Amino acid sequence: RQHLLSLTRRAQKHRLRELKIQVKEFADKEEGGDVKAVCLTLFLLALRARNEHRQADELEAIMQGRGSGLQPAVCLAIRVN
DNA sequence: CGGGTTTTTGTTAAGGGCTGTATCACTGTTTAAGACAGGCCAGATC
């Protein structure tokens, strides 16, 4: 009810229960059973309102499996060679 | 001192997805250096 960095996982849960309600219903009725992409783009927009295309591109990269992730074939290459 | 409230918290059990750590089967394929005690030959000696 006060802040969120100190509010725990379920404290935040009870804080935005109704946020979750609306977002899940709208998502799984509009995108035909999906919440990942809609919450993804929601956070992208709500952070890009502060024109932080650096973090936007970084998050789109981690969603695209390229950057600070080392896809398992790469780590396997390193362990072998 | 309370006392309605917040503000956050504690709890239940099924099943799964994930992760971290323990466990498992398994591989080496005789020493060498030095101390001491017999025992038996082997020579020095009466």
Image (cartoon, rainbow, N blue to C red):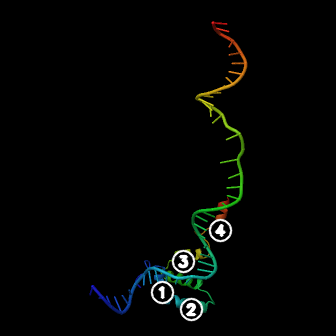
**Residue corresponding to mark 1:** A16
Q: Residue A56 carries which label?
A: 3
Place of residue A44 in the rendered image (x, y in percent of width and height, measured from the top left): 54, 81
In the displayed structure image, the side of residue A32 where residue B10 appears, left or right: left
Quarter where residue B22 is shown = bottom right
Q: Which chain is mark 3 on?
A: A
Task: Indicate which label's residue lies in the foreground, 1 or 4.
Answer: 1
Task: Name the residue that disc number 4 marks.
Answer: A72
Tag nearer the camera, 4 or 3:
4
> Could you tell me the amino acid type at mark 1?
Leu
- Same subunit, labels 1 and 3: the answer reads yes
> To which chain does the residue with label 1 belong?
A
In percent of the image, x 62 and y 89: which residue is there? A31
Q: Do the residues labelled 3 and 2 touch (CB within 8 Å)?
A: no
Q: Is disc 3 in the same subunit as disc 2?
A: yes
- Which SS class for mark 1? loop
Q: Where is residue B27 in the image (x, y as percent from the top left)?
A: 71, 51
Mark 3: give few (<14), some (14-19) or many (20+) Cα within 10 Å: some
Mark nearer the N terminus (4 vs 3): 3
- Residue receiving disc 2: A25
Tell me which numbered mark, 1 or 4, is placed earlier along the sequence: 1
Labels 3, 2: front one:
2
